[PDB]
Image (cartoon, rainbow, N blue to C red; front, side, top):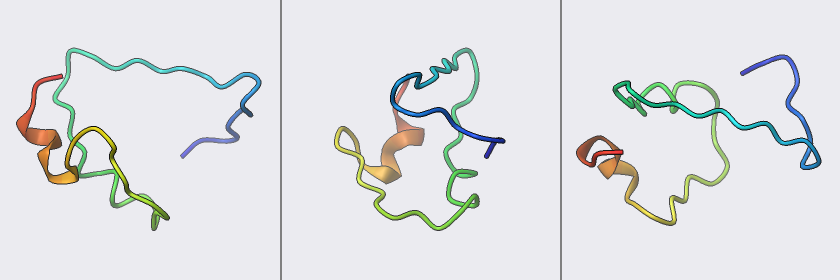
Length: 50
């Protein structure tokens, strides 16, 4: 949730580390269209180390 995101020409990158990756606040932002994680299960993000 920001002012305006860039297009695929200048897609910005934001790295996050050294913090407890809590993915529970993501579901409380807006109704999503496709929550398909192709690498891990959606209920397994808080059980693995990143």
